[PDB]
Image (cartoon, rainbow, N blue to C red; front, side, top):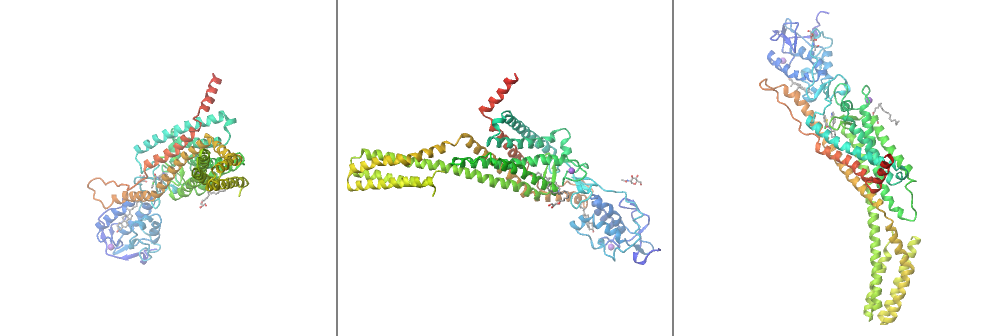
Amino acid sequence: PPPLSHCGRAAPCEPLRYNVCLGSVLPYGATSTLLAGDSDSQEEAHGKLVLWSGLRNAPRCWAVIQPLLCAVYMPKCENDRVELPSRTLCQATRGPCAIVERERGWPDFLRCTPDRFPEGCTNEVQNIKFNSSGQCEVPLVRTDNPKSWYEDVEGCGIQCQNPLFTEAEHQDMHSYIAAFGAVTGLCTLFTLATFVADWRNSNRYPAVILFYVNACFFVGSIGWLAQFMDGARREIVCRADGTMRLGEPTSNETLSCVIIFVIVYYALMAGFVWFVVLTYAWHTSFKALGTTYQPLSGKTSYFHLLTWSLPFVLTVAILAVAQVDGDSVSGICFVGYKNYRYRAGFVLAPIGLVLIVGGYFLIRGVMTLFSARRQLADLEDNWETLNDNLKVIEKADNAAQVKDALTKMRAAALDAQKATPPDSPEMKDFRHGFDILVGQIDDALKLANEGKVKEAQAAAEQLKTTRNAYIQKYLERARSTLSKINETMLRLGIFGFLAFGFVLITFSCHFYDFFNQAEWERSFRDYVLCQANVTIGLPTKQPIPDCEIKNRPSLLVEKINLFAMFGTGIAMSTWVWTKATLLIWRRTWCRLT
Ligand SMILES: CN[C@H]1CC[C@H](N(Cc2cccc(-c3ccncc3)c2)C(=O)c2sc3ccccc3c2Cl)CC1
Ligand SMILES: CC(C)CCC[C@@H](C)[C@H]1CC[C@H]2[C@@H]3CC=C4C[C@@H](O)CC[C@]4(C)[C@H]3CC[C@]12C
Ligand SMILES: *[C@@H]1O[C@H](CO)[C@@H](O)[C@H](O)[C@H]1NC(C)=O
Ligand code: NA
Ligand code: NA
C-alpha cells in the first residue's frame, strides 16, 4: 500500500554525496546516517563501506550483503523520513555471512532485531541491481559446488595445487617420488618374476611370505607412479572445478582418486599384515625345534584370511565415512589428508598395532634364540668342567686335590641340573640323571675327606659311566636342536628387523604429522583471513603487503617417510639376491637362446 508507518523512521534528510553505493547508482538523491550506528557523517559511512567491501572474497556472502549494507549506510531519506530495511533482507545474510559473526561479530545495528529490521518492508534496494558476484583471494579459487567450499568462506575452495608449497618444491618432491617409486617397482617386479619362474619350489613357507610382501610393494608402486602419466596427476588430485579433491567418494566426480586410494592404501595395509605374518613365521620357526613340527602350511588359511580381509574392512570403512582426499605433492589420494583425526585411526592405529604385534614376535623370537644359545653354552661349560676335573682326579697324588676337583664337579652338576632345553617326562629323567651323579660325587667326596685317595679315584671312574649313560645322550640332543637353526631362519629375522625399523620410521613420520597438523591448519586459516583483512584498513600508497604462513608440513619428514615406505620394498626385494636365483635367470636365457 502507500508507505507503512512502521517501515520507516523520522530522520532529517541530507542530499547524497555519492551517486553510487558499492558499484551501483542509486534511484534516490537523499540519505541519512541514522541507520548506521558506526557512522555520523556520509564520508564516515562510505569509509565503513570500504571496510565491508573486504567481503568481496566470500562471494556467497557478498551477493547478499551488498543490498543490506546500502539499505543501512546509504538508505533513502524522503521528506524527513528514512526508509528502514526489511527483516528478510537482513536474515538472508546471517547464513552465508557467518564469517562476520566469527571474526568480529555483527554490530548491534546489523543484527536482525524486529525494531531495526521490520517485517515486510519494500526495501528499495530490491530495485537496485548488484552486478558484483565476487571473487576468491589466493589461495582460494572460485567455485559454485558446495562440497568444495573451505569452511565459513562459501564460494571458494582451496586450489588443487597445494598452496603450502612452491612449484619448485613440488617438482623436487616429484623427482624424489619418481626415483624411489621406479627403483622399487623394478626391484619388486624382478623379485616377483623369480618366484613365478620357479613357482613349484618358490610357493613354500616362509619364502612365499616375501612373495606376497613384494606383491604388495609392487601394486603400491603402481598406484604411486600413476601420477607421472601425462595429465594423470591432475585427474587424480584435482576436482572438475580446480579445487583439491576432498571427501571422496563424492557423487559427480570420477573414480580416478578412489581407484588410486584403494590401490595404495589396500596394498599398504596388506603389506603391513604380511609383515606381521613374517614376524610370526620367524617366532614359530624356533618352536619347530620341539618334538612336534607344527606346520606353517596348516596356518596358511589363517594368513590369507587376515592379510586380505583386514585391509578390505579398513578400506571399506574409510570409503563409507568418505575420507579419501588428494594431495598434489604426494600425487596420490589417501585417507585423512584434510581430516587428520581420521588419519589417526586408519593409519597410525594399524601401524601402531603392527609395531606392537610384529615387535612382540620379533623380541620373543630373539629371546628364544639367545636363551637356547646360552643354555647350550652353559651346559657345555659345565660338561667341560666335569671332564677337566675328572682328569685332575685321575692324576691326583693326594686327597686335597681330589676333594677340590670333586667339589667343583658337584657345583657344575647342580648348575647343569638347573638348565632346560628350549614336571615333563623328558625333564624327569634329565634332572634324575644329575641327582644320581651329585649323589655319587657325594660318595666320592666322603672317601676323599676320610683320606682314601685310591677309593675316591676309583669312585670317580664310575662318574664316567653315569655321565655316558644319561648326561651324554641329552647333551647331544641339545647340540642337535641348535644345529637345526638354518641360515634361512636367521635371514628371515634379519629381514624382520630390517622391515621393523622402516615401520618404526613410518610410524614416527605419521605421528609427527598428526601432532603438528592442527597448527598447520590454523596457520592456513590465519593466512586466508590475513589476505582479506590486509586489503582493507590499509592506505592506497604502496602495493598491499603479502601475508605469510607461520608453519607447514616438513618435506624432509615426507621424504623420510617415503624413503622408509619404498626402502622396505627395496630391502624385502633382496630376499632373492642369492646364488640360486642367478641360476634361474641364466637357465632361462639359454632356453631362449
Ligand atoms: C602424511 N603427510 C601429510 C602431511 C599433511 C599434508 N597436508 C594436509 C592436507 C592436505 C590436503 C588438504 C588439507 C586441508 C584441506 C582443507 N582444510 C584443511 C586441510 C590438508 C597438507 O599439505 C596441507 S594442504 C592444506 C590446506 C589447508 C590447510 C592445511 C593444509 C595442509 Cl596441512 C598431507 C601429507
Ligand atoms: C575469508 C574472508 C573474506 C573473511 C574476512 C572478511 C572480513 C574483511 C570481515 C569480517 C568481519 C568484518 C567486519 C565486521 C564489522 C565491522 C564493524 C563496522 O563498524 C566496520 C567494518 C567492520 C570492521 C567489518 C570489516 C570487514 C570484516 C573485517
Ligand atoms: C553488469 O551489468 C552490465 C549491464 O549494465 C552487463 O553488460 C554485465 O554483463 C554485468 N556484469 C556481470 C559480471 O554480470
Ligand atoms: Na548513526
Ligand atoms: Na567418486
